[PDB]
Amino acid sequence: MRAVILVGGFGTRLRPLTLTTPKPLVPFCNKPMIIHQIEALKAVGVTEVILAVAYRPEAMKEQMDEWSRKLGVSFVFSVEEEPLGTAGPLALARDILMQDDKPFFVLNSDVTCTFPMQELLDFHKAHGGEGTIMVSQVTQWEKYGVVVYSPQNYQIERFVEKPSRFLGDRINAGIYIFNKSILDRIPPRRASIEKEIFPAMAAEGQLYAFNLEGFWMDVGQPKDYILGMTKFIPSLVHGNRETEAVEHQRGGRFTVIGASLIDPSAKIGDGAVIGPYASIGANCVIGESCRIDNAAILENSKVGKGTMVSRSIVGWNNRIGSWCHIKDISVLGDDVEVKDGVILIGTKVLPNKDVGEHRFEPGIIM
Amino acid sequence: MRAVILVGGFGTRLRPLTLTTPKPLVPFCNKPMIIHQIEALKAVGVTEVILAVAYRPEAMKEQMDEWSRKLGVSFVFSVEEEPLGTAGPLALARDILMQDDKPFFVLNSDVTCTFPMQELLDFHKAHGGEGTIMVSQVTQWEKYGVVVYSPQNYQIERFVEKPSRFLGDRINAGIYIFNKSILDRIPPRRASIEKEIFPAMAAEGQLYAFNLEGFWMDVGQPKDYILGMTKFIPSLVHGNRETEAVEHQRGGRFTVIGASLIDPSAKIGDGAVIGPYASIGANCVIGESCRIDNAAILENSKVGKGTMVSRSIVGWNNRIGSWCHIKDISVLGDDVEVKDGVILIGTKVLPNKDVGEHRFEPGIIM
Ligand SMILES: Nc1nc2c(ncn2[C@@H]2O[C@H](COP(=O)(O)OP(=O)(O)OP(=O)(O)O)[C@@H](O)[C@H]2O)c(=O)[nH]1
Ligand SMILES: Nc1nc2c(ncn2[C@@H]2O[C@H](COP(=O)(O)OP(=O)(O)OP(=O)(O)O)[C@@H](O)[C@H]2O)c(=O)[nH]1
Ligand SMILES: [Mg+2]
Ligand SMILES: [Mg+2]
């Protein structure tokens, strides 16, 4: 059995970070998102993964996906295309899917969860998609705006965008399983599985919902990125090698106030405070008395002594000043450098910039 | 004789347009900037041009520079590198320059002028650089911040940044001519010609200034892009095939208020008003009653009927609404689509966005 991961898309909401690498390859915790999904699929037993590459065709996806050497998994990489929407890549890859009898998985590269994939053995009871429209309970379904009306029969009546009445709380979770006959329904053109194929499947009564018991988060926005990190790190602390601690003696003496993820190659200064649900990338350097409250530090980033970055993301090769505060939901680009004493309250800095001025209001640094 | 054009750099000031293509390849009027410079160099008699390619090593610069088939000129493309500053590429290309007796040109991909290149035959009077630090008279030298003190002996005393006293009005013009011995001075590392090599040359007394009689503009910024286009189009109106008109009967019946540049393949509405110093790209479609006041329309961009874009730049594959107003200095990305009735007053929109809200103040749309 094989899977198909939608690895295209421009990453508009995660723009300051996706101007350098595609959205699937943006490191979540200490690994790319697609790597988490591929690890889950391999744990299931899927050996073949089909990547629908539109953004950065060969510059980034093919080169950086050397993980095929690891993980004992192989990627087809034969869905190179122009932008064909969410559903078009399946129409393009109908040939490589071979239209075999065995169903196939479909995933978005932006969803994080416990990945309960027992929907393979389960939900085979006469479904066009074996519980394909997997749904998660969110109390904020107004702003999410994609509500799935799943009854006890699991037959999807309709899809409602921003419904006024309390039709339901379940929302789409971005994980699907399809019988290959769906390849006949999808036309060879730009289309959206969410707004074209799925309403038709719901009308025909071949669309079935799957309830998600565990946590779920679509980490495709910086705020959702931070909150998904908070939800996810506690699950992964015992999974990996990264008292109230996860990595408490990596460099000198520093304090951890809960779950975190510090790479073995990262250097942490003396008296630093790596706070709860914080990620430190490889080869990263952290100053003496830094405070990484809820921040993600990516790759070869350097943070000076006394800096406090909280609920914020910093790019791959930053050089943060000494006594800075990067607060709120602030995202830094690939090679941003911040001078000492600069305060960034939820400001997004584009790659290859130098910041030397305080910004106390949310905004964008060109 | 051979030239070296510094085609690297991240294009930070032209960021909304340089997130898709490198700064040299950003179309100025109806051609890339580097193409204007290469045409001037070919008019000189220069056959070899060496491009210092750092940004987009092979994705854009090598593929898009198919102009080598045209123009009767050849480019070396042997300076692929990591970011080495403004002076380092010369050290890297020392080997391909062969250290021959003949001098060589140096140019930036951000400058537009009449290109007086008679500085080859002139200024040979015992100069390390034959009038290498070419200077132009600008009354706004304070904000430009690079003032060159050129006396009647043309020996550069010093370089002053934001001078309080009126030392001089001449500023750097970005065109240089060096004897190959300078390759010994430049170290094989990241350096800047403007802030490392040039002060040393001025102190040594081997730096000579060349005055620029004609117009000049560093068009690396959208405001400077628009103003330099205004300065430049009157020079090029008679040069190319694009009463008080330049292209007055291309599509239907429309009015031209002055100099402009309308590509032969562009269809220009019916009753539209293509204003003074306006550029319309190839395959572009213009609505019935548009007002292209001082705007540049790039490539396959479509503009609806009644839209008024003034002193603004639209991207390559835009789809502008019908009754919009894109005023002030506004820059649109590669694939921005604007809904009908939207007003953008000097707002920079990143590529692959959809604009549906009025923005009456300068800002950035992520
Ligand atoms: N292959 C491919 N996948 C896509 C495309 N557009 C979206 N996707 C997938 O859809 C999921 C989420 O969409 P993204 O493109 O990441 O998010 P976005 O950039 O805000 O754009 P949309 O969600 O499409 O409005 C991700 O799995 C994407 O990989 C596309 O044009 N081609
Ligand atoms: N090869 C190369 N050329 C550069 C580099 N940086 C600047 N240049 C050249 O210097 C000129 C103007 O600089 P740009 O980089 O375009 O402008 P910018 O992006 O605002 O950055 P700076 O002017 O360098 O501060 C252009 O000719 C560039 O090609 C570089 O790192 N490598
Ligand atoms: Mg998403
Ligand atoms: Mg410039």
Image (cartoon, coloured by chain):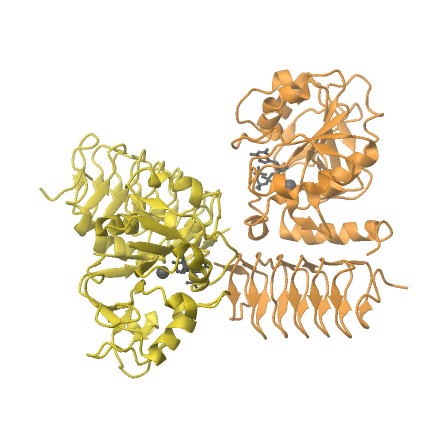
Chain colours: A orange, B yellow
- Which residue corresponds to the image point at 27% horizontal and 81% vertical from the top-left? B167
Q: Position of residue A249 (x, y in %)?
A: 84, 67
Taking A26 as reference, is B317 above or below it?
above
Viewer-proximal residue among A200 and B191: B191
In the image, is A172 to the left or to the right of B18? right
Taking B7 as reference, is A212 above or below it?
above
Taking B347 as reference, is A270 above or below it?
below
| Quarter occupied by residue A280 | bottom right
Q: Position of residue B213 (x, y in %)?
A: 17, 65
- Which residue corresponds to the image point at 81% horizontal and 33% vertical from the top-left? A117
The furthest residue to the front: B101
Q: Position of residue B94 (x, y in %)?
A: 43, 59
- Which residue corresponds to the image point at 78% horizontal and 34% vertical from the top-left? A41
In the image, is B215 to the left or to the right of A317? left
Residue A203, can we see it? no
The furthest residue to the left: B243
Residue A60, can we see it? yes
The furthest residue to the right: A243
* Quarter that holds the N terminus of chain B: bottom left
Taking B156 as reference, is B53 above or below it?
above
Number of numbered discs overlaid on the protein picture = 0
Q: Position of residue A103 (x, y in %)?
A: 75, 21
The furthest residue to the bottom: B165
| Quarter occupied by residue A307 | bottom right
In the image, is A1 to the left or to the right of B38? right
Image quadrant, ligand 4: bottom left
- Which residue corresponds to the image point at 82% horizontal and 24% vertical from the top-left? A123
In the image, is B119 to the left or to the right of B317? left
